[PDB]
Image (spheres, coloured by chain):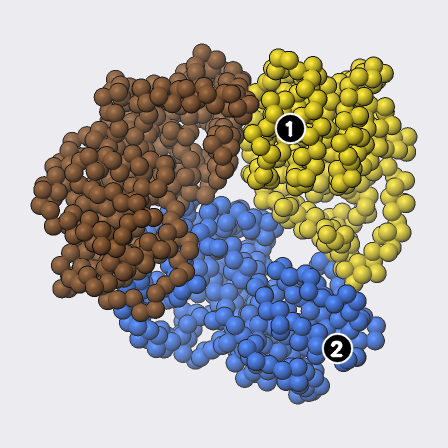
Chain colours: A blue, B brown, C yellow
């Protein structure tokens, strides 16, 4: 495994930084020089891995095409910054997050092997063709048919005309998918010659403290859309509403950076309110976990053996909700409606059902069997001379 | 000649980065080492040139004296960062944007030639004295006579006591003016022993996303407020109002960065609306161009041979509007008061008038004759050993 | 002596940057390699010193426990950035601001001497034991059961379990305190085997634009709150009211970047108003200085021999106000309550009282005797190899 040059590229967004931290640390511990290109705003997390931070300015922070336009601008701006950074310091292999595909373009120009690191499930080969009509239902908007023209023009300018705008990005050379197969929708339609389901990349055990039950709390709940974004005030009060007059339960509600006030000047020991909680520490001793369905929270709930109440909002979240529902460990709620009775029902049932608990035990064993960081590091070292 | 070290210094502001991009790229293509010092927020544009990014922290983002205070802070902060970056890596020549005159101070301290790169027209040798009372009649405010004292003190602190606060900044040793002489007010008062009118610095067209005329469109119009920030929602509706019931014409409206909200239900088939358009690509098929009168849009409208309807607001835009009006290729409107009937009239006259078209052909010919990037690069290379 | 590598670490806040600029410049002027690790937002001040800027991303930008969490995150984020930057370029000594104690953790791992640079007075080792109940009465909030415990866990990760979370931070090996002893509360309870009172670190008589006196002003006054930020417009009206009635005085009022919205008339010829003035330059010709009591402003008024009217607002300013009042060179006012009559008396009396002028002359003499930048640089060079 001759020490070689490994270049990791990602973006500052939280869901694209944490999933691969322990994988990068393992590559450093094996004697390789690892450079990590990301925005300096996440220099703390990058440097803690032990990798060389290679700073670049990220352009990432309403319309559907507008969201695609911002992502294209970041790719256009990202590529020259990596080229200047690595021109005289070329790596043996390029690792890149799903949103850092400009790194693949650089690898193709220099004849260097590249590996995609997917922080969540990938799009199946039948899923691409199924979404092809929406592409033509985007070219009649004069905005969607200028975005793709700009995208194809950028690929031609960047020295890779013989590849599709879909193939580049969503059809990598080789890819490491950091979710287990049972959290990947339509996994049988995913070609495992190309994609490898690794599962999460973990490392011994995290620190930042502990969190034990308040005495006389029989069942513990964590409600946190805390992967990143929260803002739904009416639903939060319903959570305190449900757990009010419900003793033996302890609600640990995380309302998030955007709120801190709004509470009720007192509040029983039944409800404790934070803007941030050590989610792993609370999840280790919790009996139910309410979440938005982000892959990071679900995999953390899975690893801790805690059933989940999923309230999907964005695009990755509904599919995640169906998966854990199909695994018999979760219920799906609709943030638009939901009642305290329906909320309390999903909460009280999930914590009592012993069949749910046995399924978490099995999924916990299936989770590790996917290989984790040790399997991923061996597969990356395979690409080194 | 022989490969040397060329140091370019500019600021992140939009009008001070784009005008010289192709000039720096041309200097790199000639085998020179070109370092480009700018704020990391524009690292994408700097690196794409092929130049070595040399980061420094910019202090650039109320009142007139308040505006003068921030610009002085940036000059005070810029000089030590350039000194530290170039202390042991001194270049053969210093190139600096008009707002990066601290680079000239470094060149004077180190006996290095310096060249000012002006992205628009410079201040004439007599236009200053008409404002000289206002400058001296502002030294009556204890704000104008402490700011200059701060400016004068900084010159003494920086090792250049033998120069006026006006001379350094507004009287460079050598300067490259990136506009044609016919876009420079009072050109006869510009000493061309010192300033050289280069015109815009171009280098082929990078496509950036093509835009073909819609089939069955007689003449195409582009509405985009020229060079920097926009906010005019009511004028946007009048544009859609005018081009509604104006068939055979195709309106390409750019609503711009911010405040995009406030669409209009269906939008007629005549009007297609974007937040950003490839302005060079659209101007290639345009027959009239509505703009704010920024030098960037005007020079881009000139190069494409497209008559312009100019709606100046602040800064350079009123003077720029008179220039293109004096050239017989543009009409000036007041966005607050223009009426829908007058808008279609100014538009329909400009696109139909063949005398306007002939003047544009001549102005296109005059534009190239100023030399462009090839002349600018040749003049810069003369300052190399 | 022999040129070595000195690494300074600080934070972007203004009161943690200016106090040590001239000290770093002196260490550079003495032929040493000085690296200065700070956030790039403050790169201008770092580079002007002449030191090598070592950039790291700072997480520093109501509730007692909430403030403690944000400071811990920045310390947690700072340490790996410092380790990566200095791992193969290790310094002979680590200099660190009070808020950059992760540099001390780095120095302990590498067996390197470290020196704390305190920009203001330190906490005597009796106030902490007095603060032990507040520590005990803060662990009862279920926020009180996650934060410090996270801090203790962080020490174990960083390789320093054999040190307390309080002792590390507030009990350095060696410390340079950049205030004189008469501006340090409970100075006798401060162990000077560990802490050294240096006084401010100065360097020549600067410009900042300079400021000549207007003719026909008998005595000049400068009004500028704390050492940076304010938001209280109403107090400003009383200042011009008091002076626009003393035609013999010349007021130089600093309203601050965070206002400008709202003035009064065209302004009398007695009053000149800015959002920012060269405070050192105005102090050259001033006869009274109104301030909130920030340590930066107080030491500048003290060094200029200018009596002060102190209007404390946030933390440290009342204790600083208490100090300068006890020294017989200042009067204390409450911006919320003070009236024009009490304000005008404090201004004219302080400027007229010759006993105050004599006390200022003596304190300025006491100021220099603490050693300043030359003493501090000599003490740092002692930790360097011969």
Seen in the picture, residue A146 relative to C106 is either above or below; the reply is below
User: Badge 1: few (under 14), some or many (20 or more) residues near its Cα, within 10 Å?
Assistant: many
Seen in the picture, residue B17 relative to A313 is either above or below; the reply is above
- Work out whether residue A179 or residue B139 is closer to the camera in this orientation and state it: B139
C151 sits left or right of A307 in the view: right
Residue A304 drawn at (x, y percent): 67, 73
User: Badge 2: few (under 14), some or many (20 or more) residues near its Cα, within 10 Å?
Assistant: some
Q: Secondary structure at mark 1?
A: strand
A197 sits left or right of C274 in the view: left
- Work out whether residue C178 or residue C164 is closer to the camera in this orientation and state it: C178
Identified at 63% across, 42% down, the residue is: C82
Same chain for the residues under marks 1 and 2 in the image: no
Identified at 52% across, 58% down, the residue is: A13
Query: In 3D space, how far apart are the residues under numbered discs 1 and 2 (Cα atoms)?
Result: 55 Å
Residue B21 drawn at (x, y percent): 32, 38
User: Which label belongs to residue C271?
Assistant: none
Quadrant where the C terminus of chain C is found in the figure: top right
Seen in the picture, residue A235 relative to A79 is either above or below; the reply is below
Identified at 67% across, 29% down, the residue is: C240
Residue C237 picture quarter: top right
Residue C86 picture quarter: top right
Residue B35 drawn at (x, y percent): 39, 33
Q: Is residue C385 visible?
A: no
Q: Chain of mark 2?
A: A
Residue B157 drawn at (x, y percent): 54, 17
Q: Chain of mark 1?
A: C
User: Which label belongs to residue C253?
Assistant: 1
C266 sits left or right of B365 in the view: right
- Work out whether residue B122 or residue C339 is closer to the camera in this orientation and state it: C339
Residue holding disc 2: A244
């Amino acid at each position: 495994p001759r020490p070689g040059h490994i270049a990791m590229v990602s973006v500052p967004s939280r869901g694209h930084l944490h999933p691969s931290l322990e994988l990068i640390r393992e590559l450093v511990a094996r004697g390789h020089r690892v450079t990590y290109a990301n925005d300096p705003s996440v220099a703390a997390a990058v440097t803690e891995t032990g990798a060389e931070l290679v700073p670049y300015t990220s352009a990432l922070p309403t319309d559907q095409i507008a969201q695609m336009d911002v992502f294209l601008d970041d790719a256009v701006g990202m590529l020259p910054q990596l080229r200047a950074a690595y021109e005289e310091d070329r790596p043996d292999v390029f690792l890149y997050d799903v949103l850092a595909y400009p790194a693949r373009v650089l690898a193709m120009n220099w004849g260097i092997p590249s590996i995609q690191i997917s922080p969540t499930w990938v799009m199946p080969e039948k899923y691409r063709e199924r979404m092809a009509p929406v592409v033509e239902q985007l070219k009649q908007d004069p905005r969607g048919a200028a975005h793709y023209r700009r995208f194809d023009a950028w690929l031609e300018d960047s020295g890779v005309p013989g590849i599709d705008a879909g193939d580049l990005v969503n059809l990598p050379e080789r890819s490491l998918v950091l979710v287990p197969r049972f959290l990947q929708p339509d996994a049988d339609d995913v070609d495992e010659k190309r994609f490898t389901f690794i599962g999460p990349c973990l490392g011994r055990r995290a620190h930042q403290g502990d969190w034990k039950r308040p005495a006389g709390a029989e069942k513990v709940a964590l409600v946190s859309l805390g992967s990143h974004l929260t803002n739904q005030l009416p639903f939060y009060e319903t959570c305190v509403e449900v757990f009010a007059a419900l003793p033996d339960w302890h609600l640990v509600l995380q309302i998030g950076r955007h709120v801190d006030a709004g509470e009720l000047g007192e509040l029983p020991p039944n409800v404790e309110v934070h803007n941030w909680v050590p989610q792993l520490a609370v999840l280790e001793q919790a009996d139910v976990f309410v979440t938005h369905g982000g892959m990071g929270g679900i995999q953390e709930g899975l690893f801790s053996g805690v059933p989940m109440v999923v309230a999907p909002q964005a695009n990755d979240q509904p599919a995640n909700a169906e998966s854990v529902v199909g695994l018999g460990i979760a219920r799906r709620i609709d943030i638009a409606t939901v009642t305290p009775d329906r909320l309390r029902a999903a909460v009280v049932e999930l914590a009592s059902d012993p069949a749910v608990a046995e399924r978490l035990s099995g999924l916990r064993r299936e989770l590790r069997a996917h290989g984790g960081t040790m399997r991923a590091a061996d597969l990356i070292e395979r690409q080194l001379p």
